[PDB]
Image (cartoon, coloured by chain):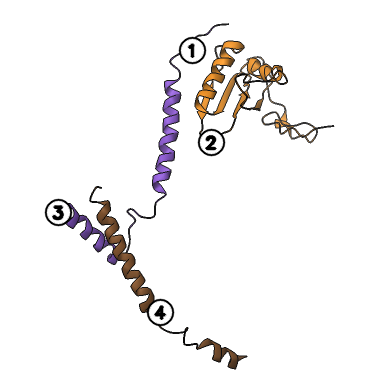
Chain colours: A brown, B orange, C purple
Amino acid sequence: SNRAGYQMRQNVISSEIFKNGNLNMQAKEEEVREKLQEERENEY
Amino acid sequence: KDTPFMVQVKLPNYKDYLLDNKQVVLTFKLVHHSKKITLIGDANKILQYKNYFQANGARSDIDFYLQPTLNQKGVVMIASNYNDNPNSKEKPQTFDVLQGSQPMLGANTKNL
Amino acid sequence: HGYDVSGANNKQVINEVAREKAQLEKINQYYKTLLQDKEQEYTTRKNNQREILETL
Protein backbone atom coordinates (compact mmCIF):
# COMPACT_ATOMS: atom_id res chain seq x y z
CA SER A 1 0.00 0.00 0.00
CA ASN A 2 2.89 2.36 0.63
CA ARG A 3 4.37 1.34 -2.73
CA ALA A 4 1.13 2.13 -4.55
CA GLY A 5 0.97 5.37 -2.59
CA TYR A 6 4.52 6.13 -3.70
CA GLN A 7 3.65 5.46 -7.34
CA MET A 8 0.50 7.62 -7.08
CA ARG A 9 1.73 10.43 -4.80
CA GLN A 10 4.55 11.57 -7.09
CA ASN A 11 2.65 12.13 -10.29
CA VAL A 12 4.06 14.54 -12.85
CA ILE A 13 0.83 16.53 -12.53
CA SER A 14 0.95 16.79 -8.73
CA SER A 15 3.24 17.28 -5.71
CA GLU A 16 5.23 20.19 -7.08
CA ILE A 17 5.42 24.00 -7.10
CA PHE A 18 2.00 25.52 -7.67
CA LYS A 19 3.32 28.53 -5.79
CA ASN A 20 4.11 30.42 -8.98
CA GLY A 21 0.90 29.08 -10.52
CA ASN A 22 -1.23 30.74 -7.88
CA LEU A 23 1.21 33.64 -7.45
CA ASN A 24 0.34 34.81 -10.97
CA MET A 25 -3.35 34.48 -10.07
CA GLN A 26 -2.67 36.56 -6.96
CA ALA A 27 -0.87 39.17 -9.05
CA LYS A 28 -3.72 39.53 -11.54
CA GLU A 29 -6.13 39.64 -8.60
CA GLU A 30 -4.18 42.55 -7.13
CA GLU A 31 -4.15 44.26 -10.51
CA VAL A 32 -7.89 43.95 -11.06
CA ARG A 33 -8.40 45.22 -7.50
CA GLU A 34 -6.10 48.11 -8.44
CA LYS A 35 -8.19 48.97 -11.51
CA LEU A 36 -11.34 48.41 -9.45
CA GLN A 37 -10.28 51.06 -6.96
CA GLU A 38 -9.24 53.21 -9.92
CA GLU A 39 -12.77 53.16 -11.29
CA ARG A 40 -14.05 53.46 -7.70
CA GLU A 41 -12.36 56.54 -6.29
CA ASN A 42 -12.36 58.30 -9.56
CA GLU A 43 -15.84 59.09 -8.21
CA TYR A 44 -15.67 58.24 -4.50
CA LYS B 1 -60.50 44.77 33.39
CA ASP B 2 -58.51 43.66 36.46
CA THR B 3 -57.47 40.14 35.44
CA PRO B 4 -54.03 40.37 33.80
CA PHE B 5 -53.26 39.07 30.33
CA MET B 6 -50.86 39.69 27.45
CA VAL B 7 -52.72 37.70 24.84
CA GLN B 8 -51.48 37.73 21.24
CA VAL B 9 -53.89 37.80 18.30
CA LYS B 10 -52.79 37.37 14.70
CA LEU B 11 -54.46 39.42 11.99
CA PRO B 12 -54.46 38.25 8.36
CA ASN B 13 -54.70 40.35 5.24
CA TYR B 14 -58.13 40.03 3.58
CA LYS B 15 -59.56 42.39 0.96
CA ASP B 16 -60.90 45.57 2.58
CA TYR B 17 -62.82 43.90 5.44
CA LEU B 18 -59.82 43.60 7.83
CA LEU B 19 -61.46 41.27 10.39
CA ASP B 20 -63.77 38.28 10.58
CA ASN B 21 -67.34 37.81 11.72
CA LYS B 22 -65.93 34.41 12.62
CA GLN B 23 -63.47 36.25 14.88
CA VAL B 24 -64.68 39.72 15.85
CA VAL B 25 -66.15 39.50 19.36
CA LEU B 26 -63.19 37.53 20.71
CA THR B 27 -60.75 40.06 19.33
CA PHE B 28 -62.78 43.02 20.48
CA LYS B 29 -63.24 41.83 24.07
CA LEU B 30 -59.48 42.05 24.56
CA VAL B 31 -59.15 45.52 23.07
CA HIS B 32 -62.11 46.80 25.06
CA HIS B 33 -60.89 45.38 28.36
CA SER B 34 -57.17 45.80 27.85
CA LYS B 35 -54.92 48.60 29.04
CA LYS B 36 -51.87 48.56 26.72
CA ILE B 37 -51.92 47.01 23.27
CA THR B 38 -49.15 46.85 20.71
CA LEU B 39 -49.10 46.34 16.96
CA ILE B 40 -46.42 44.70 14.82
CA GLY B 41 -46.56 44.71 11.06
CA ASP B 42 -46.85 46.95 8.04
CA ALA B 43 -46.85 50.70 8.57
CA ASN B 44 -50.19 51.84 7.17
CA LYS B 45 -51.77 48.56 8.24
CA ILE B 46 -50.99 49.11 11.91
CA LEU B 47 -52.00 52.75 11.43
CA GLN B 48 -55.43 51.86 10.14
CA TYR B 49 -55.80 49.16 12.78
CA LYS B 50 -55.12 51.71 15.50
CA ASN B 51 -57.61 54.00 13.78
CA TYR B 52 -60.18 51.22 13.50
CA PHE B 53 -59.88 50.08 17.10
CA GLN B 54 -59.93 53.60 18.54
CA ALA B 55 -62.81 54.59 16.29
CA ASN B 56 -64.85 51.45 16.87
CA GLY B 57 -64.48 50.25 20.41
CA ALA B 58 -61.37 51.30 22.26
CA ARG B 59 -60.95 54.03 24.85
CA SER B 60 -58.70 57.03 25.23
CA ASP B 61 -56.03 55.60 27.53
CA ILE B 62 -54.79 52.45 25.82
CA ASP B 63 -51.44 53.98 24.70
CA PHE B 64 -51.17 52.06 21.43
CA TYR B 65 -47.59 50.87 21.04
CA LEU B 66 -46.65 50.61 17.38
CA GLN B 67 -43.48 48.90 16.17
CA PRO B 68 -43.55 48.58 12.38
CA THR B 69 -41.78 45.98 10.27
CA LEU B 70 -41.14 45.26 6.59
CA ASN B 71 -41.33 41.53 5.83
CA GLN B 72 -44.51 40.64 7.70
CA LYS B 73 -47.39 39.06 5.81
CA GLY B 74 -50.17 39.96 8.21
CA VAL B 75 -50.09 42.00 11.38
CA VAL B 76 -49.95 40.74 14.95
CA MET B 77 -51.34 42.48 18.03
CA ILE B 78 -50.58 41.93 21.70
CA ALA B 79 -53.18 43.08 24.22
CA SER B 80 -52.05 43.46 27.83
CA ASN B 81 -53.96 44.43 30.95
CA TYR B 82 -52.07 45.75 33.93
CA ASN B 83 -54.29 45.71 36.99
CA ASP B 84 -53.67 49.22 38.43
CA ASN B 85 -56.65 49.00 40.81
CA PRO B 86 -55.86 49.98 44.40
CA ASN B 87 -57.84 47.52 46.56
CA SER B 88 -55.77 44.34 46.89
CA LYS B 89 -55.03 43.01 43.41
CA GLU B 90 -52.24 40.43 43.72
CA LYS B 91 -51.00 37.87 41.19
CA PRO B 92 -51.74 34.20 41.98
CA GLN B 93 -48.37 32.38 42.40
CA THR B 94 -47.21 33.27 38.81
CA PHE B 95 -49.24 30.15 37.75
CA ASP B 96 -46.79 27.29 38.03
CA VAL B 97 -49.66 25.03 36.99
CA LEU B 98 -49.84 22.10 34.60
CA GLN B 99 -53.62 22.30 34.31
CA GLY B 100 -53.94 25.93 33.24
CA SER B 101 -51.97 27.97 30.76
CA GLN B 102 -50.13 30.95 32.18
CA PRO B 103 -51.89 34.25 31.44
CA MET B 104 -49.10 36.06 29.67
CA LEU B 105 -48.74 34.12 26.43
CA GLY B 106 -51.32 31.38 26.40
CA ALA B 107 -49.88 28.91 23.86
CA ASN B 108 -53.26 27.22 23.58
CA THR B 109 -52.94 23.48 23.05
CA LYS B 110 -56.49 22.09 23.03
CA ASN B 111 -59.01 20.20 21.08
CA LEU B 112 -60.30 18.30 24.09
CA HIS C 1 -67.73 57.00 18.75
CA GLY C 2 -65.40 59.71 17.42
CA TYR C 3 -62.92 59.97 14.53
CA ASP C 4 -60.18 62.12 16.11
CA VAL C 5 -57.21 60.84 14.08
CA SER C 6 -54.30 63.05 12.98
CA GLY C 7 -50.76 63.99 13.90
CA ALA C 8 -49.75 60.70 15.58
CA ASN C 9 -48.49 59.20 12.31
CA ASN C 10 -45.39 61.22 11.42
CA LYS C 11 -43.68 59.61 14.41
CA GLN C 12 -44.67 56.23 13.01
CA VAL C 13 -43.37 57.15 9.56
CA ILE C 14 -40.14 58.24 11.28
CA ASN C 15 -40.03 54.76 12.82
CA GLU C 16 -40.53 53.15 9.41
CA VAL C 17 -37.77 55.22 7.86
CA ALA C 18 -35.49 54.39 10.79
CA ARG C 19 -36.03 50.67 10.18
CA GLU C 20 -35.43 51.44 6.50
CA LYS C 21 -32.18 53.19 7.42
CA ALA C 22 -31.13 50.16 9.46
CA GLN C 23 -31.86 47.84 6.52
CA LEU C 24 -29.87 50.12 4.23
CA GLU C 25 -26.94 50.09 6.63
CA LYS C 26 -27.09 46.29 6.75
CA ILE C 27 -27.14 46.13 2.95
CA ASN C 28 -24.20 48.55 2.77
CA GLN C 29 -22.35 46.52 5.40
CA TYR C 30 -22.79 43.47 3.18
CA TYR C 31 -19.75 44.22 1.07
CA LYS C 32 -16.57 42.41 0.13
CA THR C 33 -15.03 45.05 -2.14
CA LEU C 34 -14.76 48.37 -0.25
CA LEU C 35 -12.58 49.38 2.70
CA GLN C 36 -11.35 46.54 4.93
CA ASP C 37 -7.87 46.76 6.43
CA LYS C 38 -5.53 44.42 4.59
CA GLU C 39 -1.83 43.63 4.29
CA GLN C 40 0.71 46.14 3.04
CA GLU C 41 0.76 44.78 -0.52
CA TYR C 42 -2.94 45.55 -0.81
CA THR C 43 -2.95 48.81 1.11
CA THR C 44 -0.01 50.54 -0.57
CA ARG C 45 -1.52 49.78 -3.96
CA LYS C 46 -4.82 51.13 -2.58
CA ASN C 47 -3.32 54.39 -1.32
CA ASN C 48 -1.45 54.81 -4.60
CA GLN C 49 -4.66 54.38 -6.61
CA ARG C 50 -6.38 56.98 -4.43
CA GLU C 51 -3.53 59.47 -4.85
CA ILE C 52 -2.84 59.00 -8.58
CA LEU C 53 -6.58 59.04 -9.15
CA GLU C 54 -7.22 62.28 -7.29
CA THR C 55 -4.55 63.74 -9.55
CA LEU C 56 -6.33 62.15 -12.54
In this view of the protein, which residue sits in the foreground, A42 or B51? A42
Q: CA distance from mark 4 to mark 1?
A: 72 Å
In this view of the protein, which residue sits in the foreground, B68 or B78? B68
Relative horizontal placement of residue B97, taking residue B65 as reference (left or right): right
Q: Is residue B15 visible?
A: yes
Residue in the image at 50% along x and 26% along y: B43
Disc 1, SS: loop
Disc 2, SS: loop
Q: Chain of mark 3?
A: C
Relative horizontal placement of residue B90, taking residue A37 as reference (left or right): right
Quadrant in the picture for residue C45: bottom left
Which amino acid type is shown beneath numbered disc 2? Answer: Asn
Q: CA distance from mark 3 to mark 2?
A: 46 Å
Extreme top residue here? Answer: C1
Q: Is residue B65 visible?
A: no
Residues tagged 3 and 2 counted as in contact (Cβ below 8 A): no
Extreme bottom residue here? Answer: A3
Q: Residue A29, relative to residue B91: is it above or below?
A: below
Q: Chain of mark 2?
A: B
Q: CA distance from mark 1 to mark 3?
A: 58 Å
Label 3, on which residue? C55
